[PDB]
Image (cartoon, rainbow over all chains, first blue to last red):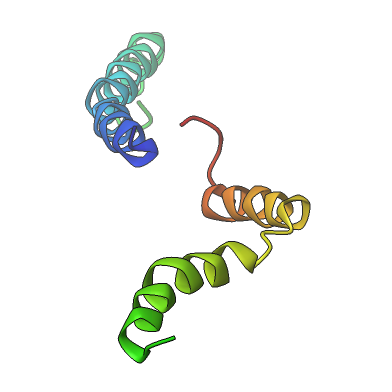
Length: 50
Length: 48
């Protein structure tokens, strides 16, 4: 049985993890940018600084 | 003994025997094979 056929199919499946993985980074970026905006409401009294 | 009858002996008695005579030296042949399977694989792994 083709050793390389196994590898061929797997490599297809592994590549499919790029989507949900990049998405994850974005979901983190979202929570991070939300948090810096949450914190900086305590500095709102200074418009140019915030 | 005639020529043509001898030819039959060449074809069906000599030729087979000449073939049988070339020794495999299998122990050294088996080594060749084992080396061969490791080399096709090599940098890849295992099954199948």
